[PDB]
Amino acid sequence: QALKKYTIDLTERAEQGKLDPVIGRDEEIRRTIQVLQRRTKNNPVLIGEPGVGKTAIVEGLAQRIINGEVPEGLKGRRVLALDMGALVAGAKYRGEFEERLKGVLNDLAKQEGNVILFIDALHTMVGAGMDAGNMLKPALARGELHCVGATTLDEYRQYIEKDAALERRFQKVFVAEPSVEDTIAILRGLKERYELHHHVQITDPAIVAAATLSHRYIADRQLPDKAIDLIDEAASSIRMQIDSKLRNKVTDAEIAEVLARWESEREKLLRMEQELHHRVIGQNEAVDAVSNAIRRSRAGLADPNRPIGSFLFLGPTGVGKTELCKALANFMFDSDEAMVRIDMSEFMEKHSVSRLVGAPPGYVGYEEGGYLTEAVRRRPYSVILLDAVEKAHPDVFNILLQVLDDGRLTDGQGRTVDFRNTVVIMTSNLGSDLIQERFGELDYAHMKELVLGVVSHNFRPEFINRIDEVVVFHPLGEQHIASIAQIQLKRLYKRLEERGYEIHISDEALKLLSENGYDPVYGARPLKRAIQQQIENPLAQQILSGELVPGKVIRLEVNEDRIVAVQH
Amino acid sequence: QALKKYTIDLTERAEQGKLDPVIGRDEEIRRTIQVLQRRTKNNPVLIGEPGVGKTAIVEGLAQRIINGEVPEGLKGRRVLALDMGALVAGAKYRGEFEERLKGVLNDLAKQEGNVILFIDALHTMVGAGKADGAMDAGNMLKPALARGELHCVGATTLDEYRQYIEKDAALERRFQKVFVAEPSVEDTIAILRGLKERYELHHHVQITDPAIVAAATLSHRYIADRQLPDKAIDLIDEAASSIRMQIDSKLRNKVTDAEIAEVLARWESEREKLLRMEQELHHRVIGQNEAVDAVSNAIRRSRAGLADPNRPIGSFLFLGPTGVGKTELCKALANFMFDSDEAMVRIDMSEFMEKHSVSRLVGAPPGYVGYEEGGYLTEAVRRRPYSVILLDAVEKAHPDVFNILLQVLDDGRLTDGQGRTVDFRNTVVIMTSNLGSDLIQERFGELDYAHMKELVLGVVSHNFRPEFINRIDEVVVFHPLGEQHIASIAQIQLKRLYKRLEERGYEIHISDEALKLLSENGYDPVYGARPLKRAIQQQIENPLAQQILSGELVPGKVIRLEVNEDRIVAVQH
Amino acid sequence: GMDAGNMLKPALARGELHCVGATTLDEYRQYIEKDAALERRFQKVFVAEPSVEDTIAILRGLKERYELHHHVQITDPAIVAAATLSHRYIA
Amino acid sequence: RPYSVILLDAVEKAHPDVFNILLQVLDDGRLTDGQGRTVDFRNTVVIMTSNLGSDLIQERFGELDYAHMKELVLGVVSHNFRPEFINRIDEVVVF
Ligand SMILES: Nc1ncnc2c1ncn2[C@@H]1O[C@H](COP(=O)(O)OP(=O)(O)OP(O)(O)=S)[C@@H](O)[C@H]1O
Ligand SMILES: Nc1ncnc2c1ncn2[C@@H]1O[C@H](COP(=O)(O)OP(=O)(O)OP(O)(O)=S)[C@@H](O)[C@H]1O
Ligand SMILES: Nc1ncnc2c1ncn2[C@@H]1O[C@H](COP(=O)(O)OP(=O)(O)O)[C@@H](O)[C@H]1O
Ligand SMILES: [Mg+2]
């Protein structure tokens, strides 16, 4: 007998109750029963993205055969899972695959149509060295074999729709990936078997939180596969926490730990403006607007078919543009440089646009993606930084129309890029001196209206209609940039404590460092690099000269024109 | 029992102490027991590396079973291992080995959740049983995987997993990537201390703990084929057997680290590195001793570590005419620090004068020349992250070169146009030019080196930006080598020529006057010593190869390279 | 030609066998490092190609062997020329 | 046959990632083939033909000597080939 060498009787296993109580999927079982009762072409092929429980559909079919929920043409059938990996096992010689396969087909003809065959992973059957479609193909055609195929959508349209004969001997039954609520119903169906195996209890709020977090924070794996993965691994984790040396009920906190490893954010975002002024002082208005945008995004009030932040940053450099972006991605999601910076001074032509979107099919930069779109397809929860967007060719703003309205961009390889989890930041200088010359005792609203009119003469009318809010980036005064220099001295003290030194300063040295490179026309970044050079050259040179010892009072005392470092 | 016929019980051997004690790997055993006590995905597979203790994790698991340190669910479990050739011992018939394997699987179904099966080289067992009118191992165990009658534990390399188990469907979703980390040095020390007693009681010798840390450190430092911790265990046991041979043939038992060094060489850093540097410089490169000492100072100030490691090591402008061994200096730096000739990067910037500079060098925009090429600079450092970079002819640059140079001298870490992150801080960046070389060819004589350096640095400040050259470590001067260094380098060329002629079977000594004719004919201030090489080739070897084939020069004579009025002649005496 | 390896390879995990192996680098890299069920029963004795010195020594001993067969006087310049010219002009 | 003459005729028509194979050849004389091994090229005479300075040499060979013409057409070749490659040529000649 060749069936017992290679098949697995599913209905006999469901008779002993080893299979899963498949709950749901009723219309797919009904369409499969419609297919298996035709005259010719009785062969459904279950098609969907992987993980969605297609073997579960055939297990439910076998359980309906055991119970008798089938029509009066399927009572008494046997469902036999065939193993295409097992027929190509000893493929040494000529005509040894065909011996096994013809033994299977003779024994299926022997049963007089009483056996539903289940050939999972149907893409195996096409390439078998002619081979394997051409012995099943006439018996598939006449409907005297009842092969329930089951294969991936992409494997189906890559292997089987290439071959039209084997394609028409089957019939598609498209399997919809289940919803979040349907996953909840699945887990409520399968709670009892896991609580009777792990001997623990499972809390139902942790179940619905597990399904919700699995659907939200995992995009590769699909429901219910990732959900039952999280439940099973948390059940085993609680099993070993009991079984080591103390809870038996799984909470959703353990679910979140398994999700992150493998809600005080509300209280943080209430003080998010304080969090943004933790690292950059001054520029209250952009802090308020960005904190409002993040609060509306985490509150979910905003339209979820839009990006988070459409913000046109203006004004001269060094007023706290990129430091704000770094601390924003830090206190928002992860880090100062878990982001993307794009220098838009590069892009100045039409092939610039084809660079940042991606080359079309048949051209040079095709297989190596775009530049924007690849950088976002790597990091879907990130921050996009367009350095000097005014320097661009004027058609890049058409791409950014698509970006800032729809949150989707279609690269050159023909796929879409999701922008509904990132923040677009655009830096410009179209009104820098206009705000510098009129910052004194002129308010925020009229300055915004003036620079809005100027940039509206600069930019297209379609693109200015897409922005959430255009901040001004007013020039900071003497005490503001002096406090910025104080913050730079504090983070320099942090870096030297990372180096392992305790270095003091004179207040006169602080005043000279604040008055080295102060300019409202370029920002604090000349002041930053001036302090950086005038400290990192002589002090770290005296470190390399063999003077400084970790644990001595090191006062940055003033010279006549310089700053001397002492050892006391 | 067919299990008692040709399978291996590991728990009986751990109960009888016939196995290796395992110290470490607590996290991996804990995650393995997380993976085992499930209902779906019951079988783990130990993805590891060739020699990182994949067998030792299951050995320690069986020892925790015997010692009862396991959780309650795995108490009483008997881990039986699967043995290949024992099952293929007496089985050649049509259906004898396969019937044996089926009886093994019937026994595994019979024990009813009591036996964990362990299979080393899982992919091999899936592709082993090449029989006739029969079946293999993989597609007979494959029913037992997705039927719950097997609590299997796998062990394989990552690559054969990524070929043979990720490709399948049921074999994929019945197996779990319990990744095994390659252990650290001090973890290897702890493991060797856990097994020092076994080897000492075996070989009747003693093992020193400084020898243990020296063996572990130098095994991770030098050995590339094997991995931790197996190479250290092999070094310990090979040293033990070598001391046993010293007892036997031609009286010690304490294995010291000197024995480890003798075995490993038959198979320390800072000041020795400094002295080897400062000595081995003068062998290849002749002269330029100011630059020798300056590179020695830069090496000291870089490897002190007291500065910022957020900047690359090399920031050097090397000035002087061509033919002074700038390439020899770069190759000497590679020969010491990275120990090769072409452990280096030479890029000639005398062609990127136009706008197409960052495109060709760093990485091109698509639709251009360098885009289907990779990148002359950043993809070169992708090829050699651990190397030295040379920038010839920095004076032929473009304003979109200095931007790359400013980003390098600030950071070292860099990103090309495609958008991937490179870092330069393990490398050396060397630039060269020849702007002030006319002044150096004019008045290097009767002038010093310090004010020479300051004056040519002023010339650089005429040509370059001060803040750009502010980030340079040091600029040295390559003087025009005139008489004795020319004599030495022509002597080197003649040494290799003498070596080839002596292996041919002649003996040639040059006159000093003929070497003076080489110096006057091969050296020029505008080029240096490349006309030295081609003039040596022409004026020596072409009459010499004319004469040797001529049936004139008998072996065994001192062939004096005398002088003609303007030629160099090879005479016999 | 079960035939030999399933009768001798099990003795390696039986301790009855103390064999000495000999193979090319290619068969160790193809048929033994892939054969991972037997990796820690062997040790890679990397026999290197001998240099010109050891070649000349081996050729002197085998000169003493070969002069009983060809009945010739092999001269030592021919030995050093054989070692050198075989090292250079044959890859 | 290790002692042959290798003619690489009209080499400037080739695609510029064929010259890297020839960089291996003119660097070391060993060349890694497809099957894996290496082939000793240190007994061959590798001769390449090209005409990259056609208009230049037809225009200016009069009133110019051999060395300056070699320098000028070598600069043209430097625009075409690599300087990593034509440094490894033993002797460019100019017709
Ligand atoms: N309607 C359902 N009722 C009960 N369990 C389900 C249901 N849908 C899916 N599952 C479970 O989800 C998992 C999916 O099992 P499989 O059918 O083997 O996976 P799949 O959906 O077929 O995807 P592939 O391509 O076979 S990996 C199993 O644990 C099923 O028990
Ligand atoms: N000190 C030296 N010792 C030995 N050979 C040397 C020495 N200096 C120069 N040479 C030789 O002279 C050659 C000159 O080559 P280069 O180093 O390229 O000359 P250069 O002065 O660096 O001019 P460029 O810019 O590199 S073309 C070297 O390749 C060596 O063969
Ligand atoms: N912690 C440990 N305790 C005991 N033995 C160990 C330990 N780590 C490594 N070993 C030894 O090193 C060897 C390496 O094992 P493994 O990585 O499984 O080899 P392979 O990679 O060839 O399968 C083991 O056979 C074991 O004897
Ligand atoms: Mg399936």
Image: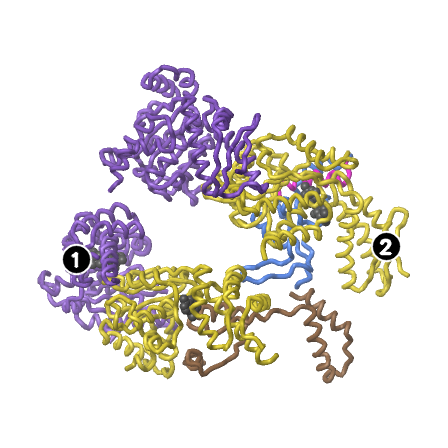
Chain colours: A purple, B yellow, C brown, D blue
Position of residue A415 measured from the top left corner of the image (x, y, whole percent)? 34, 42
The chain letter for the residue carrying disc 2 is B
Residue stretch rendered in magenta on the structure: D64-81
Alpha carbon distance from label 2 to label 1: 99 Å
Judge whether residue B424 can be spotted in this image: yes
Assign the magenta stretch its main secondary structure: helix
Q: Callout 2 environment at 10 Å: few (<14), some (14 to 19), or many (20+)?
A: many
The chain letter for the residue carrying disc 1 is A
Residue B496, numbered label: none
Q: Which numbered mark, 2 or 1, is in the foreground of this view?
A: 1
SS of the residue at dot 1?
Answer: strand
In this rendering, is residue A256 above or below B204? above
- The answer to which image quadrant residue B142 occupies is bottom left
For this view, does A303 lie left or right of residue B127?
A: left
- The answer to which image quadrant residue B14 occupies is bottom left
Residue at the image position 74 percent from the left and 73 percent from the top? C79
Look at mark 2 in the image and give the residue it sits on: B561
Q: Quadrant of ligand 1?
A: bottom left
SS of the residue at dot 2?
Answer: strand
In this rendering, is residue B424 above or below B92? above
**Furthest residue toward front:** A568
Residue type at the position of mark 2: Leu
Position of residue A426 measured from the top left corner of the image (x, y, whole percent)? 38, 30
Look at mark 1 in the image and give the residue it sits on: A201
Residue at the image position 36 percent from the left and 30 percent from the top? A398
